[PDB]
Structures are given as C-alpha cells and as structure tokens.
Image (spheres, grey):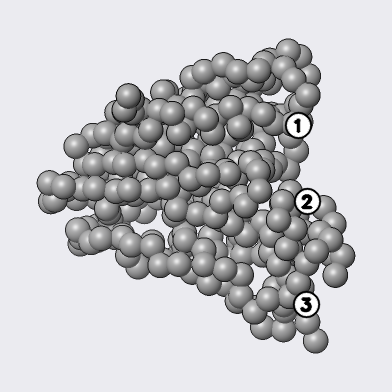
C-alpha cells in the first residue's frame, strides 16, 4: 500500500571534517522540528574487487571526496584559454 | 595540533545556487551531448558565459538537490576497472528522502527499488550484457562515509542506509 | 566544436575552495586540526 523505507538517523555534534583532516564540535539543536525534504539526484558508489570479470559484482555506497560532488555537476564543462 | 574555540553559533545553513562564469581570459565550453559520458571528444559543444544553476550540497553516498540525466541513467568513473575508484551515478528520475531531527529519514520503497534495477542495468561490467549485480553496504570507515551524512536544517545527520544498499539483481 | 573534456575539472578545484570558504563563513564550530 504505502510501504516506505524508514532509515534510522542520528544527529552528531563531534564530526570528522570534509574540508581538511580535522575534527569539529557544534552546539546541540535548539529546534524541535528539524525538517528536510531533499531530492536524491544521484549516487556515488564503489565496487568489490578480487572478482574481476566474474559472475557477480558487489557495489557499495561511497562518497567522502566532496570534489566528486562538484564533478557530477561540472562534468560537461571546461575552461579554455581565450585571447 | 591547533584547537580553535570560536563562539560556536546556532545559524541556519542554506544553499544558494552558484553560477560559475568565465574566469578572466578563458572561456567555458559546455558539452551539449545530452548523454555526455565523462572523458572523451565531445561532438556537440558550445561556448557559454556561465555554467548553470549549481546547488552546492555537501553530503555523502547520495547526491541531492542536483542535476538529473535527461535521457537515461548515466554512470561515470575515471577507471571502471580499478575497484578503488569512485563511480558516480546520474539518475533518470528524482527520488525523495524526507527527514526530521527525530532520528529518521523515509524514502518511498517502490520509487527507490526501481532506480536500483535501472542502475543495475549497467554496472561495472559496463552496461554489461548480463551478470549478477549485488548491492551491499559500506565495509567500514568514518561515520560520514559509512552513513548518508548531510547537513539538514543546519544540523548534522548520520542516516544508517543498510536498507538502501542490500539487495541482489541480474 | 569537436573538443575534449574529462574527469579533471573546470571548477572542481575552484568550487571546492569556494565551498570550503563558504562553509567557514557560515557554519562556525570549535575546530581542531592536526599539523
């Protein structure tokens, strides 16, 4: 009928930075109605190895290099030197 | 080992579509090939003053609020052979993921299982004629890597996604 | 026409630095980085 994929989620305050190799801590929430509605537009995967060209291929979620996030939008572009 | 104590403030982070235009004596060349696939000699192409409305969303394993493929699901990687390299996937249709600070994110079961078989219709083998495609979840590593981490309403969410990547197809 | 593009950039390195510098001005924490 209306089967939805419920994913357990957690709000952390101490995080490993994505900018550079660091750690950061933010204040706890103040709002009691944090609400987001995003549109999955993609996926960033990775494949299991040691089974090259064989019958199965395992693919797991990935991410981490935020560059790979800009790359998905900028792929079709390029800067050429103009006179 | 630099520690910095700033007046940690409760602000609200909002994404402003960023347009990137031509930098100095350079020119931006947009490839118009509806299904341009990464590296290669783009046939249909043209100069532009600025790219397009790019929404800088920081998050893991799931690209959100961005550009979709206008034709079919297109994947891209530097080397589809080296298992160590990230494979980006551009989706055909958008999927929704509604989340709240109350600890959960729900996404339509049907909508997402469909995109999975679509992505499955072309994995590593390279749109391979056929073989078994398996979706498992993260092997391990940082919380931001092992879970769909993102900044929702200013707060940092770490959504457990074992349920999105745990299935088998052919 | 008939040009070349790839898994390199345009604004990948640029944008990355704009966004890193955008986050800094916005979401301020209490940082800790290792030199």
Residue B121 lies, with reference to residue C7, above or below; the image says above
Does the rendering let one see residue B75? yes
- Indicate which disc residue B39 carries: 2
Q: CA distance from mark 2 to mark 1?
A: 15 Å
Residue A82 lies, with reference to residue B94, above or below; the image says below
Q: CA distance from mark 3 to mark 2?
A: 19 Å
Q: Callout 3 environment at 10 Å: few (<14), some (14 to 19), or many (20+)?
A: few
Instruction: Provide residue B39's location: percent of width, then percent of height.
Output: 78, 51
In front here: B128 or A73? B128
- Indicate which disc residue B126 carries: 1
Q: Are the residues under badges 3 and 1 in a single subunit?
A: no
Q: Chain of mark 3?
A: A
- Give the left or right position of residue B150, taking residue C30 as reference: right
Q: Chain of mark 2?
A: B
Q: CA distance from mark 3 to mark 1?
A: 34 Å
Q: Secondary structure at mark 3?
A: strand
Q: Secondary structure at mark 2?
A: loop
Does the rendering let one see residue B142? no
| Res A79 quadrant in image | bottom right
Which residue of the protein is positioned furthest toward the top in this rendering?
Answer: A55
Residue A22 lies, with reference to residue B105, above or below; the image says below
| Res A56 quadrant in image | top right
Quadrant of the drawing holding the C terminus of chain B: top right
Instruction: Provide residue B75's location: percent of width, then percent of height.
Output: 66, 41
Q: Are marks 3 and 2 in contact (CB under 8 Å)?
A: no
Instruction: Provide residue B42's location: percent of width, then percent of height.
Output: 81, 59
Residue at 58% of width from left, 27% of height from top?
B117
Q: Callout 1 environment at 10 Å: few (<14), some (14 to 19), or many (20+)?
A: few
For label 3, the residue is A81
In front here: B37 or A18? B37
Q: Are marks 2 and 1 in contact (CB under 8 Å)?
A: no
The residue mark sitting in front, 3 or 2, is 2
């Amino acid at each position: 009928g209306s089967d939805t994929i419920t994913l357990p989620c957690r709000i952390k305050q101490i995080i490993n930075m994505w900018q550079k190799v660091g750690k950061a801590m933010y204040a706890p929430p103040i709002s009691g109605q944090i609400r987001c509605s995003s549109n999955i537009t993609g996926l960033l995967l990775t494949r299991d190895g040691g089974n090259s060209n064989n019958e199965s291929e395992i693919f797991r979620p990935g991410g981490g290099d935020m560059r790979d996030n800009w790359r998905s939008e900028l792929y079709k572009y390029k800067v050429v030197k103009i006179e | 080992t630099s520690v910095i104590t700033q007046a940690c403030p409760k602000v609200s982070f909002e994404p402003i579509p960023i347009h990137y235009c031509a930098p100095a004596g350079f020119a931006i060349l947009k490839c118009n090939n509806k299904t341009f696939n990464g590296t290669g000699p783009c046939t249909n192409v043209s100069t532009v003053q600025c790219t397009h409305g790019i929404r800088p969303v920081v998050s893991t394993q799931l690209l959100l609020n961005g550009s979709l493929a206008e034709e079919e699901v297109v994947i891209r990687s530097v080397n589809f052979t080296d298992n160590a390299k990230t494979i980006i996937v551009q989706l055909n249709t958008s999927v929704e993921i509604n989340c709240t600070g109350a600890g959960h994110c729900n996404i339509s079961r049907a909508k997402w299982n469909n995109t999975l078989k679509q992505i499955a219709s072309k994995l590593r083998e390279q749109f391979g004629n056929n073989k078994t495609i398996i979706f498992k979840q993260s092997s391990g590593g940082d919380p931001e890597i092992v879970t769909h981490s993102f900044n929702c309403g200013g707060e940092f969410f770490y959504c457990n996604s074992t349920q999105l990547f745990n299935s088998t197809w052919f | 026409t008939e040009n070349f593009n790839m898994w390199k950039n345009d604004m990948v390195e640029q944008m990355h630095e704009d966004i890193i510098s955008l986050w800094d001005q916005s979401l301020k924490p209490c940082v800790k980085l290792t030199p």
